[PDB]
Every structure is written in structure tokens, then in C-alpha cells.
Image 1 (spheres, helix red, strand yellow):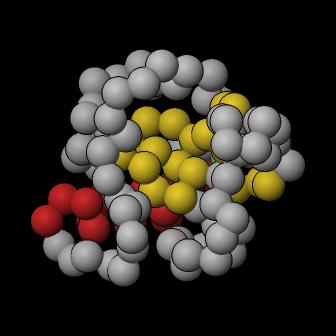
Image 2 (cartoon, helix red, strand yellow):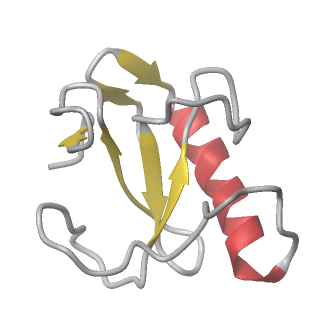
Length: 106
């Protein structure tokens, strides 16, 4: 969580940290802030994984602040099941449904 640029959509170390500290407070055991599915365990599949442990979960970001639910939501920050930032991925530079890594994430 140190200034991630998701292709074109820039996110301050403040924004990554805000969304993650939020995702953290919500996914642990305090509130069910709207959401159809997010946050929820980023279970199985290849393509992407983070050098940590998990089980990690998704939290889709926005270029304004923490969780709004505007749609689309290509840009998504992903955390660990405590309070640690896993990485930041986005559909920005991807093939529609696919994903790519933001600045720092690889």
C-alpha cells in the first residue's frame, strides 16, 4: 500500500490504505456494509496470487474514496484475513473480464 497506479487510474498510498483499513474492519467481524459479494474470499484459480498466505479477499476500489458500488469495478484492492494489503489488480489494461497488476503488484 504505497501509491498504486492501476494502468491509468491512480490511487494514493492514502486511498489504498483507506480501502484496505475499511475492507479489514468490515471482513473481520464488524458490519455487513451493503455488497452483493464484496468482501469475499478470493478462492482458487490460476493467473493471480500474492506472496503472503491468506486466505485473502477482494475489495473493489473507486477513484473517490472507500466502497461506493458505482460499476464498472475493474480496479480492485485485495487484502489478507487480518488487516494486511495483499496487492492491487485491475481490468484497466486487461482483456475485459481478465486482470493485470497495478504499480508494485506483479
